[PDB]
């Protein structure tokens, strides 16, 4: 039978996919990740599929790997599915041709997401699914959560009966992450629809040595074409099969579908053709406008491939005179996007009435497609009739955009209550909204919808919840813009974001703040808000959620209080039932540790209900004094681009505001100054031993060491306390540790590792520190950084260099950023960074925040993110460029040495040439050439003068996480390191795919809990270091900051100076590991990681072998027996102990045994006397030679594959035997 | 000057590609292998391109690696090329979106070959080039050994001046391996057709720590769409 | 019923032997990432690599399996880097069965390895 | 399963055109490279001999365990194990937690003690 | 009375240049695609040509 539930598109389709598949080969990619993870969870819980079995699910190394596995499973006779999107779908394309080419019933469920071009987007659009429209897969689109469920079922059933693989897709986030109350079928109902005859035929034709066949032959021109057309019959029948299953499923659900469905006026004159979630919004607008008499309609595309023109026309009103086809993609240079071209083709082949056809583009990267935009589209059809337009953006560059009137009337059905909640990261707002949706949906007949907007910031980010409740189906697939209820859970937002925008008149505005008194409110509430509340007669409520939570014992935790506010004031339910239901549920959930935790929550509810009174305000708010504008100084770019985006106005930036190639300038994060740390450090100079370890360790570059001369401290604020500098080389300098309180994330690592027993750093509330430190950091920032005093690569001296990566969006206490920041302090001014997609690319470059910056001379890391799978090859390419361009420069230089260039110029050239690959010398002489050739514009000296940005030796680095290095990019990494070229690979090992949600990677350790290893990973951690060391010519090393900063610096210097490939693997802590005492213990955890023997440190240096010494050196000591407490101090290990104590004990013992063995193997490596030795190069010499020249026998075959321009000469093809056999035969045949 | 020679489509194309590129990341795949092998032998023989330099050619682990290297070389300011077909071109698709997306003057010379479906085939058809039509690469076809030479040259010249990568393609075997007596141009002649200012501009906007920028950001719904339409003036 | 279903699954009665055949170009280069992951999975599969020390079919191009000094396409003056040690790399797992064979040297060791690997 | 190099490598290589053609075209480099190959295999065999002589090797666990069930790595974690990102968003995510913006457990507790009030 | 339009620049597809090569006398036009996209309403070149005639409106 049926069953109601409130869930998202992902779960709705995974529900069906699990039931219908026996095997799933998967790989994580947002926003489809949820499906694979649920399937895994259900298989582990014991959920049965229609065959009464738990799903066999395996995580591959990439989507390409998953696609080949899917093909193998299907070829081998097992119903198979996979979940993917965007970049991942692209990697599956080659196997798609094979899966459809071999008529296999596979089903791919795709959360349609944008492809990375000028930029990467995890958001929704059809660029990915259209990229695969030629693979031969049938394509069924679902446009709503309820449809994702239905279409997923049709796809599987039709795939099984048709023998044509299906791609079931729905919009990324807009449908995959939207919550709706829907109806799902029982697995037994799905099972009943399966064509048993077809299933048996599938089984019988599959690969099997009992009745084998050959698949995947290589064919010549004589038969290939015929073989390709032999599947025709199958594709002619899929449409009818899809129709029949839509009907068979409908008889069970009551929901009918056609390949193309029509809604709107039967006599519509203007019709839109669309696909995906846009269809719901368009329909909602049609109901509204048609009720006013407008003759408009919409054709919803269900089956996109095969494209059946007959079914399309069956849905087209004869009265349509103008048709607009909406494509949610962009194919540069094409005469029109996919859907548009298909529709145009239908009309030309029909050969009759040709209504006006227009093409429109919308929703790229989940761009809003709101009711007003639909109005634009319909108005365009009766108005200008612009063709190839875009809607949702202002294209002031090519003028392709339709103007959009946002005063358009709200079109949600009568009786819909709309809500918006503004929350702060981890304050539980989203969780309570999802709970509120469940509660309301399970206890009323109301339809409920939820959608959530998050922040690119991983910590202290702002969240915005959009909820809708109604007596009628909610087709609003766009954000709420005219809310009945608006709640701001963070009082900090009040002054910075337009929180009451579009709120209805008489709407309810609930605010969390301690401004209970009218004077306090008048003191904080901006004029604009007061005027808005006033002029709209808003039901304004204020509630000190933090005081109530504290008092009832919930310790400032506000979720329950704000939750109560919603259930009481939103008005979707009567008070009695609400408070009732809310309470019943508190007992449901919680109900754990005694009735005490239940009491506090229940009490908090009653206290909330009571204290929840309408804040009364003076009519004088009608015109509160429009405040001035105490806006600090920044730059034009931050003023005109990033600030607008950070304040959520990016949607208003026209196309003219962006660089055609998507680039961004460095350093835009310098001005964010978010100030979201709860507690920040306070320097206690009386205990400071002036070590610079606190600055070295900061994950956000929030600590600024200061070394000034007396003169530089004259205009210094009174509180700018500075110690006289310790150290011989610092005699006479004044030292200060300046805390950047607004950029601090308040993790506590600095304070945690500050050497002195009597700490020089103590955590304190941000407010107790900002007034003094803000003007202090400001002043210190203008003090020249003393980079020339101490060695750049010394612990202390490194912190006297300019950090070139600051204030990133990484989590508070992130274990990756400290390493990167230091790397820039050592090479920043001359590095190229090819960054693999992952956390490091996300905190590294989530527009509009750019943490990497330039130094005082304008030099900084040239940073780029290509893809997730190609970081190494990307960096190798940059290295090829430098080789080619610098070789060109060298050639010009030698050339100019043989000319009448001046003695000085020649000295410089000769100097540069000799020190070409030396950072010190190439810069020394390049800087002379810059001076010496200044102005030179002609001839040879002119070309050399124009290549100055190539004078100093560059440092190419490849940054990537473990998922990249051990999995998807391993092949690339391996090849690049094997090239022997001069590149540097820095792997930030978090032992999981962090960014995407903690999925297991081959870097995940034995027994660690992570997605797809939820019972603890049952294979040991892949030994990347030892695998790379077998080459002998690659510098390999491991590091752990918390264990030894010096060893880290030593490794950086040795790896970078190695004239060949270098691989550095760093232990990076991460919130996914669940450090028990907080991330502020990362350094200490890194310390233990090494002491326990879990993460041994070593260095493999090939040049030592070149000089007779052992290249391998251990840098840490044998395991000290602390591994158990090390593991148990991380939830990724502790959860297993609490859930499966028996296996967890076993797995922790296995880990201790693994590390013990590994260390002993490393000890012998370091003791060995036998080692691979070799020189840096030697050889080359102009010239080439073919492997076949002068061979005694044919060296190439008779194939089209080996044919070359010069091939074809006669030769002995080995059909007459050996040279000796032929000789002996010759003597024997003397005659 | 012009020179009368008797060769096939691969060679006629390779003749030009070598002259116009500084860097090449290759991977072998019939029927385009001949091109990369020729480029490699010529570089090893010391042949000079239009900059008087021998080509910097490296063999990657696959075409995906070759395409990522090509993207990196172009991003770092080196005129770059590659040769491929069929299954190999499919592997380059992810990077193709990035190369065109970042308006890079890359040039792929493709010997159009069938895609493996019910069977593999090393022979010619446009299945592969059509699979890459939405990548944003301009696509210029040559229908004869003589046009392969001419379009190859046009593709390079146009990619440099337009900042839109080009895919120069011709029929696998039917053109790539057909031998014809044709005319080819001297490298000097090709060099004189190059837009020197566009080229200087390509190098000045390339990745360099001396004057850095960030490329390949991650963008939200607020600006992605605008950012994708920003390249219209180029197309 | 049940016996009918079981009767219909007879082509699954006998334990099967899953083999993956490929050359050095596949195993050392393009398919290395996948080969590596599949071996790390710990599942019962058998990989048999026919190492010709070049991409043979396509015309003798070098691969990471090509040895130092061997001439091949893209190694026209002799390859200047040594052969990649795929065997020792995979042995680092500890749970993968790895072996090398050479028929001309020992047909018996070849047969012994087949039996042990399978 | 085989023995130490018997010294026939030079003849081995020179009997194959892939090596000999180099000898005829770039005699000097070829000489170097064949000696390099001889050194490479000498070392490798020596490394394999130690591998065969070692007493250091790790246990072999085929399979076994699974323990019908699974758990999320964030379950019962003291601090948030996921970020505010749409990438980490999941159906069951959204519950309040300590986002590490207030410092260590120890640092937090001490600030409590120090601000007793 | 027959003709042939040779496609040089397939992308970007410029309809103006396509029509600059089309004879006004052409009553029937066959578009040949050297590919197969199973289930598509037509192959790539054909689809592009159709769009050209549809947008022209003549
Ligand atoms: C071809 C392909 N497959 C999948 C993805 C999805 N991605 C991943 C699985 C990356 C996880 C990174 O792992 P690791 O270990 O290298 O780094 P770290 O732990 O530091 O994060 S983040 C990323 C993205 C942004 O698109 C998304 O889907 O969230 C992708 N970009 N490309
Ligand atoms: C993605 C991709 N890149 C390139 C090729 C081209 N192919 C190769 C480079 C294969 C050579 C394989 O070498 P190796 O060492 O693994 O095996 P062996 O030496 O035994 O031959 S034969 C083949 C093909 C048939 O399609 C072609 O282009 O000719 C391909 N099929 N797919
Ligand atoms: S608490 Fe963390 S973010 Fe703040 S200064 Fe210290 S190390 Fe940096
Ligand atoms: S870690 Fe502590 S002692 Fe060292 S420089 Fe920083 S504040 Fe001073
Ligand atoms: S690596 Fe972990 S701690 Fe760092 S930004 Fe990513 S999720 Fe956060
Ligand atoms: Ca190096
Ligand atoms: Mg990771
Ligand atoms: Mg081979």
Image: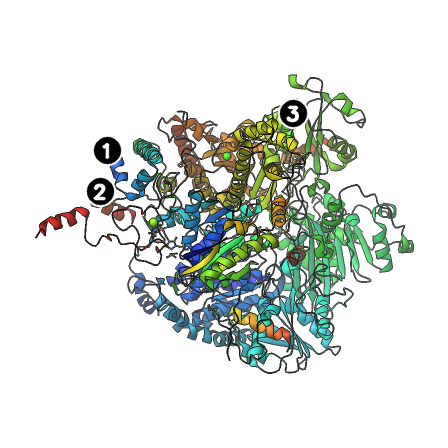
Q: Secondary structure at mark 3?
A: loop
Residue at mark 1 to residue at mark 2: CA–CA distance: 14 Å
Query: Mark 2 falls on what kind of element?
Result: loop
Which mark, residue D6?
1
Chain of the residue where label 2 is placed in the rendered structure: C
SS class, disc 1 = loop
Q: Which residue is mark 3?
A: A788
Q: Which mark is residue D23?
A: none
The quadrant in which residue A709 appears is top right
- Residue count near mark 2 (Cα–Cα under 10 Å), binned few <14, some 14–19, many ≥20: few
Q: Position of residue D90 (x, y in %)?
A: 59, 54
Picture quarter containing residue A795? top right
As drawn, the label of residue C105 is 2
Mark 1 Cα-neighbour bin, 10 Å: few <14, some 14–19, many ≥20: few
- The verdict on label 1 being within 8 Å of ligand 8 is no
Please determine if labels 3 and 1 lie on a single subunit.
Answer: no
* 1 or 2: mark nearer the eye: 1
Q: Chain of mark 3?
A: A
Q: Is mark 2 within 8 Å of ligand 8?
A: no
What is the distance, in whole Å, between disc 3 and disc 1 at their CAs? 59 Å
**In the displayed structure image, the side of residue A62 where residue A486 appears, left or right:** right
In percent of width and height, residue A633 lies at 79, 41
Q: Chain of mark 1?
A: D
The count of marks equals 3
């Amino acid at each position: 039978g049926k069953k109601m539930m409130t869930t998202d598109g992902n779960t709705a389709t995974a529900h069906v996919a699990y039931a219908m598949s026996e095997v799933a080969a998967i790989y994580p990619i947002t926003p489809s990740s949820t499906m694979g993870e649920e399937a895994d969870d259900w298989a582990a819980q014991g959920r049965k599929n229609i065959f009464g079995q738990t799903l066999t699910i395996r995580e591959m190394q990439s989507e390409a790997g998953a696609a080949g596995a899917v093909h193998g499973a299907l070829a081998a006779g097992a119903l198979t599915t996979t979940f993917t999107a965007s970049q991942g779908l692209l990697l599956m394309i080659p196997n798609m041709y094979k899966i459809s080419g071999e008529l296999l019933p596979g089903v791919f469920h795709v959360t349609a997401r944008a492809i990375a071009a000028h930029a990467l987007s995890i958001f929704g659009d059809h660029q990915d699914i259209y990229a695969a429209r030629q693979t031969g897969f049938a394509m069924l689109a679902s446009s709503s959560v309820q449809e994702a469920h239905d279409m997923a079922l049709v796809a599987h059933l039709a795939a099984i009966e048709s023998n044509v693989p299906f791609m079931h897709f729905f919009d990324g986030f807009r449908t995959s992450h939207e919550i709706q109350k829907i109806e799902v079928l029982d697995y037994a109902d799905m099972a009943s629809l399966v064509n048993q005859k077809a299933l048996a035929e599938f089984r019988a034709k599959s690969m099997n040595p009992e009745h084998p066949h050959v698949r995947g032959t290589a064919q010549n021109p004589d038969i290939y074409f015929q073989g390709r057309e032999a599947a025709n019959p199958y594709y002619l029948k899929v449409p009818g099969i899809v129709a029949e299953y839509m009907q068979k499923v409908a008889s069970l659900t009551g929901r009918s579908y056609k390949l193309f469905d029509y809604v709107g006026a039967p006599d519509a004159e203007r019709v839109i053709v669309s696909m995906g979630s846009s269809c719901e919004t368009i329909e909602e607008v049609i109901n509204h406008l048609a009720a006013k008499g407008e003759k408009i309609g919409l054709i919803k595309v269900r089956l996109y491939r095969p494209f059946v023109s007959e079914a399309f026309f069956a849905a087209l009103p004869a009265s349509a005179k103008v048709i607009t086809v909406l494509d949610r993609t962009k194919e540069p240079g094409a005469p029109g996007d996919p859907l548009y071209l298909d529709v145009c083709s239908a009309f030309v082949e029909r050969g009759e009435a040709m209504p006006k056809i227009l093409a429109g583009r919308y929703g790229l990267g989940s761009k809003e497609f709101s009711p007003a935009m639909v109005k634009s589209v319909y108005d365009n059809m009766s108005g200008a009739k612009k063709n190839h337009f875009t809607v949702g953006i202002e294209d002031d560059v090519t003028g392709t955009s339709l103007p959009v009137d946002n005063a358009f009337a709200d079109t949600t059905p009568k009786g819909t209550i709309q809500c918006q909640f503004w929350g702060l990261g981890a304050d539980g707002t989203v969780g309570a909204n999802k709970q509120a949706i469940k509660i309301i949906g399970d206890n009323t007949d109301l339809f409920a919808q939820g959608y959530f907007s998050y922040d690119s910031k991983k910590s202290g980010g702002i969240t915005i919840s959009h909820l809708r409740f109604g007596e009628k189906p909610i087709q609003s697939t766009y954000l709420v813009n005219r809310a009945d209820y608006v709640a701001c859970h963070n009082p900090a937002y009040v002054g910075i974001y337009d929180i009451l925008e579009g709120i209805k008149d008489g709407g309810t505005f609930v605010l969390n703040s301690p401004w209970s008194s009218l004077e306090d409110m008048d003191k904080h509430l901006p004029s604009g808000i007061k005027r808005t509340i006033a002029n709209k007669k808003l039901k304004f409520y204020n509630i000190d959620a933090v005081k109530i939570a504290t008092d009832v014992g919930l310790g400032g935790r506000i979720n329950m209080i704000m939750q109560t506010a919603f259930f009481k004031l939103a008005g979707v339910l009567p008070f009695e039932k609400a408070v009732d239901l809310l309470k019943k549920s508190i007992h449901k959930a919680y109900g754990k540790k005694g009735e005490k935790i239940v009491k506090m929550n229940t009490d908090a509810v009653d206290q909330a209900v009571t204290s929840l009174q309408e804040f009364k305000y003076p009519d004088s708010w009608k015109d509160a004094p429009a405040e001035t504008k105490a806006e600090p100084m920044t730059n034009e770019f931050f003023k005109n681009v990033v600030k607008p985006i950070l304040t959520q106005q990016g949607d208003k930036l026209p196309v003219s505001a962006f660089e055609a190639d998507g680039r961004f300038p460095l350093g835009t994060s310098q001005f964010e100054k978010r100030g979201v740390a709860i507690n920040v450090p306070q320097w206690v100079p009386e205990n400071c031993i002036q070590c610079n370890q606190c600055a070295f360790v900061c994950p956000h570059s929030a600590i600024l060491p200061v070394l000034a001369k007396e003169e530089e401290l004259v205009g210094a604020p009174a509180n700018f306390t500075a110690l006289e500098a310790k150290g011989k080389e610092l005699k006479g300098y004044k030292f200060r540790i300046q805390i950047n309180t607004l950029d601090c994330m308040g993790c506590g690592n600095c304070a945690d590792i500050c050497p002195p027993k009597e700490k020089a750093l103590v955590m304190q509330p941000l407010d107790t520190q900002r007034d003094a430190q803000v003007p202090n950091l400001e002043y210190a920032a203008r003090i020249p950084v003393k980079s020339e005093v101490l060695p750049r690569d010394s612990l202390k001296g490194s912190q006297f260099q300019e950090p070139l990566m600051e204030f990133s969006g990484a989590c508070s206490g992130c274990g990756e950023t400290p390493y990167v920041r230091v790397i820039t302090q050592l090479f920043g001014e001359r590095m190229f960074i090819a960054n693999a997609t992952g956390c490091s690319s996300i905190w590294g470059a989530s527009a509009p925040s750019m943490p990497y910056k330039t130094n005082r001379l304008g030099q900084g890391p040239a940073w780029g993110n290509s893809l997730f799978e190609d970081a190494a090859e990307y960096g190798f390419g940059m290295n090829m460029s430098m080789f080619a361009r610098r070789t060109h420069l060298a050639d010009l230089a030698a050339k100019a040495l043989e000319s009448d260039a001046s003695g000085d110029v020649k000295e410089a050239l000769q100097g540069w040439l000799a020190g070409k690959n030396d950072p010190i010398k190439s810069k020394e002489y390049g800087d002379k050439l810059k001076k010496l050739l200044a102005g030179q514009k002609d001839g040879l000296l002119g070309q050399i003068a124009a290549m100055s940005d190539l004078y100093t030796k560059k440092s190419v680095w490849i940054f990537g996480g473990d998922g990249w290095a051990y999995d998807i990019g391993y092949g690339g990494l391996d090849h690049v390191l094997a090239s022997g070229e001069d590149v540097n690979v820095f792997v930030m090992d978090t032992e999981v795919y962090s960014n995407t949600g903690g999925q297991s990677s081959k870097a995940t350790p034995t027994g660690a809990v992570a997605k797809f290893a939820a019972a603890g990973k049952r294979t040991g951690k892949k030994d990347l270091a030892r695998m790379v060391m077998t080459y002998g010519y690659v510098y390999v090393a491991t590091v752990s900051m918390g264990y030894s900063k010096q060893q880290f610096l030593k490794v950086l210097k040795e790896a970078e100076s190695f004239p060949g490939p270098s691989l550095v693997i760093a232990y990076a802590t991460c919130i996914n590991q669940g450090l028990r005492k907080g991330m502020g213990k990362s350094q200490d955890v890194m310390n233990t990681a090494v002491k326990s023997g879990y993460w041994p440190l070593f260095r493999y240096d090939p040049r030592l072998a070149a000089q007779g010494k052992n290249p391998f050196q251990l840098d840490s000591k044998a395991p000290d027996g602390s591994v158990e407490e090390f593991l148990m101090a991380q939830n990724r290990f502790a959860v297993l102990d609490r859930s499966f104590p028996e296996d967890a004990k076993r797995l922790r013992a296995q880990v201790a045994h693994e590390l013990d063995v590994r260390f002993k193997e490393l000890e012998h490596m370091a003791a060995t006397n036998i080692f691979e030795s070799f020189a840096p190069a030697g050889g080359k010499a102009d010239g080439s030679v073919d492997f076949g020249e002068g061979a005694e026998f044919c060296t190439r075959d008779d194939t089209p594959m080996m044919a070359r321009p010069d091939s074809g000469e006669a030769c002995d093809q080995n059909r007459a035997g050996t040279s000796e056999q032929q000789g002996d035969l010759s003597k024997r045949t003397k005659k």
